[PDB]
Image 1: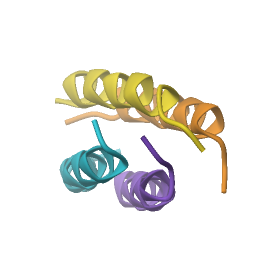
Image 2: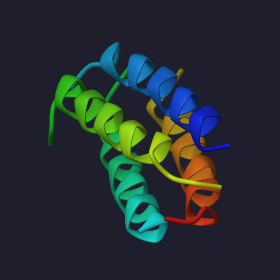
Image 3: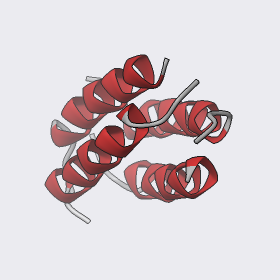
Length: 21
Length: 21
Length: 23
Length: 22
């Protein structure tokens, strides 16, 4: 599902944001 | 195209691997 | 190496493009 | 999640994206 995949990618973006350099 | 999108997602994943916890 | 924030923002823009797909 | 785990989940979803249509 395109919307379901997009939601999963956004949750992954949430996780990436909380990583360090 | 979806393949172009998937290619960019994979490139992004490569860069995420270079980050740290 | 791009920052976590720049990568996260790129990933949100790709998610918008995925959401726009049809299947 | 580790960088590794996120990157692998991204690659998993990339394959699913690859299988969609315009």
